[PDB]
Amino acid sequence: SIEDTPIVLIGAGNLATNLAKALYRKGFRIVQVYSRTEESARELAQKVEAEYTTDLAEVNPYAKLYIVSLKDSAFAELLQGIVEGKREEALMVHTAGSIPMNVWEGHVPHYGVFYPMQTFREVDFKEIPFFIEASSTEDAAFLKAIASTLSNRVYDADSEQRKSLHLAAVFTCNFTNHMYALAAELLKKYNLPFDVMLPLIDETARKVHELEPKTAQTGPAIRYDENVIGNHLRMLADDPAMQRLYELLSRSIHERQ
Amino acid sequence: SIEDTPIVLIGAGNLATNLAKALYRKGFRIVQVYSRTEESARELAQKVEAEYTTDLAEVNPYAKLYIVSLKDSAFAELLQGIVEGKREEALMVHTAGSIPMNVWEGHVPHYGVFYPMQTFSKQREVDFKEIPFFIEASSTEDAAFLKAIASTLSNRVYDADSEQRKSLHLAAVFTCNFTNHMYALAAELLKKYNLPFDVMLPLIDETARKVHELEPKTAQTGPAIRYDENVIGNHLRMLADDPAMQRLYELLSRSIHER
Ligand SMILES: [Cl-]
């Protein structure tokens, strides 16, 4: 029934490819693929038993869902040609999380954001989170049902919520890796190999699959053990920037008790 | 033979719970557990089929090894209550990264540090096989004894001084404690926007696995490298509700940028 949603793809890049193939494997009919270049459109279209076009005027107007994955400018330039000719029920979605849903506003009555947030080629979607925004509660439910066909992790998220993901990634990837870097600087200073940290790094990550971070939290800053922290701060005296960081991070941990 | 060593745990927290279970599974005899609170003493004793007490005066004086996992504030208070009436050959060890071995000196003839370095939680099982275990003792024969015990548990058993061990522990606070806090803040943020923390797990996994291949310095990604002042401005703007979290973001970004 849901796999009886005729689908058109506008764009034949990597994400589009993965998405189309996974949809096709799940039982979905992909009726047609569009791409800027002949090669790209044909190639993907051959992988999912679909027609292909290079011309927006030849895009099938009667599908239920249109998945646009074009880059910013290209998407931009071509929005009106994408919109042109589509019947009222056509659901118009784009896959880029950074592009507000309101681009479709005034052009089509049924639209949304269909954002699969991916970690890095071919990727199976069963653990990849999907973030859904739509022009209506029914359009959202439909896109969520489409996405749940491919993934166990499907959520409502507006632009503000989608920004919070990338803010959270900064903490989770950038700031975490920096902690590894500061550890490495210290072990370099003290002439101790860094490889000893690797089991601690792995387990720190592994642990929060099972426990909430707040519960997984350990160390001297929980009770604010000054016998430890005071001494650690002293060893960092020669790097007052790193020392401030140690202090502020420890207070931040302690403020959560 | 070495599994016949009767062991007492003085302290029943996260590290002690995990270390006790690993000893018990390897066939060691944990005779009893002491803790300041009945709930913690009992929970652990049931897991490792041991007696328990919350009174140091009731502590079994007949064991060969006493593993002490206590905060500083309980150490002094409780040191002589831990050490009196024991066998001359009993070994007293503590498990702290940043406490010198010399705490014991003058108090008991045999003593040492028995330090497994890993993040521990009671509700979470860990493979001891890959845990760095650092050993110091009052004599070579006591150190050989501790290492032999630790080697039944871990393939990574190392002799290290109090000075090396402090150094490792400082690096471990960054590596484990501050890293998990980054996860905690991300979770706080995601909750404020009605999103589950779990969406971060793939990225958490990638970030950790990356440093097996690359030096952390080489692995560093994100808008702080260039000091992308748009995204950084936008991000600071988002954290306006939380000045302390906002300042951390700024200094961490500043910090990446310098390096
Ligand atoms: Cl007592």
Image: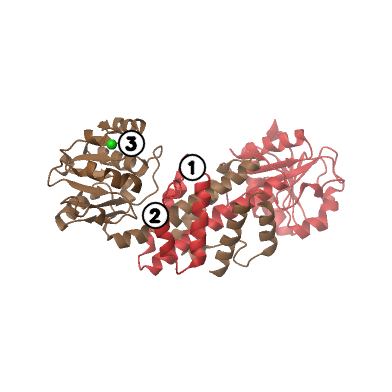
Chain colours: A red, B brown
Going by the picture, which residue comes out furthest to the front? B77
Residue A49 rendering spot, x and y as whole percentages: 68, 45
Q: Is residue A86 depicted above or below A189 in this figure?
A: above
Say whether marks 1 and 2 touch (CB < 8 Å). Answer: no
Q: Is mark 1 within 8 Å of ligand 1?
A: no
Report the amino acid beneath label 1. Answer: His
Q: CA distance from mark 2 to mark 3?
A: 21 Å
Q: Residues within 10 Å of mark 3 (few under 14, many from 20)?
A: some
Describe the element under mark 1 as helix, strand or loop: helix
Q: CA distance from mark 1 to mark 2?
A: 29 Å
Disc sitting over residue A228 in the figure: 2
Could you say which is closer to the camera, residue A139 or residue B224?
B224
User: Where is mark 1, residue-wise?
Assistant: A209
Report the amino acid beneath label 2. Answer: Val
Q: Quadrant of residue B82?
A: top left
Describe the element under mark 2 as helix, strand or loop: helix
Describe the element under mark 3 as helix, strand or loop: loop
Could you say which is closer to the camera, residue B25 or residue B68?
B68
User: Where is mark 3, residue-wise?
Assistant: B36
Could you say which is closer to the camera, residue A165 or residue B69?
B69
Q: Is mark 3 within 8 Å of ligand 1?
A: yes
Report the amino acid beneath label 3. Answer: Arg
Which quadrant of the picture is home to ligand 1?
top left
